[PDB]
Image (cartoon, coloured by chain):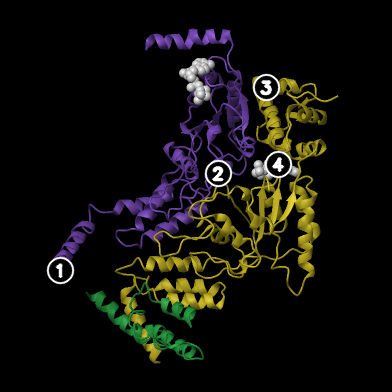
Chain colours: A yellow, B purple, C green
């Protein structure tokens, strides 16, 4: 009765002090606290904190730090996941809808997805592969992340490490500063609603160092499967649990990745396509896209011999960006010729009609 | 006590005079957020930041950061465009009165406009081209930029690369840092009022790259032909759409461009003029200008 | 001056509800510094925080550094 009557007096004085807020402030933040999570030390630290913002209303810069720290602390997911997959026959069907070929990456995903069923007595969910995909520029390394996320029914988020020179892009700044915010990883874990997404780190061989810091030293702490159980940035004081996260990183060469990161990654090399692989990719992915995006759908059509003519005589490369630029050129000039004088039915571009659209061939074929 | 008395007089008769007060700033910002654009995640972000701002101390070392951030969010463009499909003969007549010859670039622009006429009213993806123009040092590579922009009635902006070694020119800073502000691309999209300008990136093959300082790797995100739906600099913490903007870049050799950056761009050779072309250019463009001046 | 009076009376009530919460920030130190071990200079430098008392419920920017200092020291 004594603690309750004193808390009644607190409620009364705050009632004349509050204006529906200062009053509905906690039932905001404690439905936020008691609904999600949480680990016990983090909850006790947050509750030994939450009392101590009796400081606004003639103030404060003290309350606008603490309440936003509690806002960041109650919207990052604590132990809330998505259901695991039950067919490895459905994952294969979804992976074959988006890309042609690429048997090594697809089989490696199916292997590490079939290991995760058979293990009860758990050593495996602590170790998802830190996977790195290495290859020449036109091959589908970046567009393969979203398909892997869709086939396992998991959430996706891409982080681009292109020219990052700054620590506190990985970690944060401590909340004693003015505009302190957490890093990219806590922000990505907030955007994704769950604790087990797929995260793509786009060019990891391209990070820059600096005199003040080096983000590779911070990226070691994230991709280490002995430290990311207790990952801690500078904004959130509490340790945070990664390693439910499935990381995929992509790269052009291995020679400029730092040495403490190469030894903790499994490397899959992607070599570049042959001409039959490029002809299949062209026919069932690249030509319908370029026909749709130019308006000429149902009015023009290319044959297989013409696709071989384009591949052999107008491009040489490992990937497929130049091939889709040539096919888009055929679509643009088809639109131009239609808009001059229309025809009916569909015009069929045969292999002796390619220099009408593309010009003089660039490479002479071997014979 | 006297300076406290001054404090309370000034706060009273200033910010509670009634008429000449800050009715307009926060509430006009409130109504401005829900008019221009914007995507729903960005709008939720902006409204939560505004509600965070409306409880801060009068001052302030932290309210300036939030108000500057909301100003940058509200005056960058979201879904506003000067119009597409035009008359094609009128644009070829405008293109022919600024430059002699150069048939490949003119045909690329005209068949872009043909595609814009045929896809009018459909529900298909619209992606703007990304070109590089390669040639010897005197040919009209830079001069085609505002001519192509004036032909299609679009806004023009010119970023000069070359010598640039700082990565904080492409993206920005975190805005925890004190005088932070976004990169050149968001600033260029702010100067232009629309979401589809023509932006000239001039001498792209002269960016200076080493093991500390590499802005040519940050350009891989801005010129990616299907991942610049979501371009994130470090100042704005939202993904920004750079897929409608017509990029034209200029170079005079292809050897000092990195290979992943070269592979994202469509290359147009501009070879160098003959003697008959030089005589026509001198009769129609160079000698009347040098006579007038 | 009304709300100043109200903040100060509620802060009075708040530190009189801080018994064994804000009070008893010492007794882990009596548990672990009078054990086997610590020399007398460590007794001097370790009991440095008992009569620096009335500053953790008052503010502070340096309030919770006491549990940090003790949990790292003893
Ligand atoms: N097997 C494939 N089937 C279908 N499309 C493919 C295939 N391989 C590549 N592509 C397409 O190729 C395009 C370019 O692929 P990207 O992954 O974006 O290139 P990249 O792998 O990121 O390499 P970088 O970033 O230049 S080092 C995308 O539009 C993919 O859809
Ligand atoms: N075909 C042309 N017709 C008319 N004027 C031209 C033509 N080619 C070049 N010029 C003029 O030549 C001048 C120089 O052109 P610029 O575009 O500045 O050359 P540039 O290619 O930009 O040089 P750099 O070294 O590569 S930046 C301008 O005044 C142009 O108007």
Chain of the residue that carries numbered disc 3 in the rendered image? A
Q: Which residue is the site of mark 2?
A: B218
* Element on which disc 2 rests: loop
* Neighbours of disc 3 within 10 Å: few (<14), some (14-19), many (20+): some
Does the beta carbon at disc 4 come under 8 Å from ligand 1?
Answer: yes
Does the beta carbon at disc 3 come under 8 Å from ligand 1?
Answer: no
The residues tagged by marks 3 and 1 sit, at their Cα atoms, a distance apart of 85 Å
* Element on which disc 1 rests: loop
* Element on which disc 4 rests: loop
* Neighbours of disc 2 within 10 Å: few (<14), some (14-19), many (20+): many
Q: Which residue is the site of mark 1?
A: B1
* Element on which disc 3 rests: helix
Q: Residue furthest right?
A: A367
Pointer 2 and pointer 3: residues touching (CB < 8 Å)? Answer: no
Chain of the residue that carries numbered disc 2 in the rendered image? B
Q: Position of residue A2 (x, y in %)?
A: 38, 91
The residues tagged by marks 4 and 2 sit, at their Cα atoms, a distance apart of 18 Å
Does the beta carbon at disc 2 come under 8 Å from ligand 1?
Answer: no
Pointer 4 and pointer 2: residues touching (CB < 8 Å)? Answer: no
Q: Residue at x 78, y 49 (%)?
A: A96
Q: Are marks 2 and 1 on the same chain?
A: yes
The residues tagged by marks 4 and 1 sit, at their Cα atoms, a distance apart of 74 Å
Q: Which residue is the site of mark 4?
A: A136
């Amino acid at each position: 009765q004594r603690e309750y009557y004193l808390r009644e007096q607190m409620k009364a004085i705050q009632k004349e002090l509050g204006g529906e807020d200062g009053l509905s402030d906690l039932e905001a933040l404690r439905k936020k606290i008691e609904e999600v999570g949480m680990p016990e030390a983090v909850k006790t630290k947050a509750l030994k904190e939450l009392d101590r913002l009796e400081r606004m209303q003639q103030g404060s810069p003290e309350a606008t730090v603490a309440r936003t720290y509690l806002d960041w602390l109650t919207e990052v997911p604590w132990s809330k996941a998505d259901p695991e997959v039950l067919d490895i026959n459905h994952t294969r069907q979804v992976l074959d809808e988006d890309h042609y070929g690429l048997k090594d990456v697809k089989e490696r995903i199916l292997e590490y997805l079939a290991v995760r069923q058979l293990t009860q007595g758990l050593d495996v969910r602590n170790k998802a592969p830190i996977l790195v995909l290495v290859g020449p520029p036109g091959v589908g390394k970046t567009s393969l992340g979203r398909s892997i996320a869709r086939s396992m029914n998991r959430k996706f988020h891409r982080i681009s490490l292109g020219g990052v020179r700054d620590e506190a892009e990985i970690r944060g700044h401590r909340r004693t500063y003015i505009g302190a915010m957490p890093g990219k990883l806590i922000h990505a874990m907030k955007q994704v609603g769950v604790i087990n997404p797929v995260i793509l780190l786009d060019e990891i061989d391209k990070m820059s160092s600096d005199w003040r810091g080096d983000p590779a030293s911070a990226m070691l702490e994230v991709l280490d499967p002995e430290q990311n159980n207790t990952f801690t940035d500078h904004y959130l004081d509490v340790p945070y649990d990664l390693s439910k996260v499935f990381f995929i990183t992509t790269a052009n060469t291995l020679q400029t990745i730092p040495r403490p990161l190469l030894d903790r990654m499994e490397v899959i090399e992607i070599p570049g396509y042959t001409n039959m692989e490029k002809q299949a990719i062209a026919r069932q992915y690249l030509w319908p896209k370029q026909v749709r995006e130019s308006g000429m759908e149902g009015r023009i059509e290319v044959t297989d011999a013409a696709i071989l003519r384009v591949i052999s005589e107008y491009t040489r490369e490992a990937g497929v960006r130049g091939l889709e630029r040539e096919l888009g050129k055929i679509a643009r000039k088809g639109a131009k010729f239609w808009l001059e004088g229309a025809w009916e039915g569909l015009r069929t571009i045969d292999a002796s009609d390619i220099p009408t659209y593309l010009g003089i061939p660039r490479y002479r074929p071997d014979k």
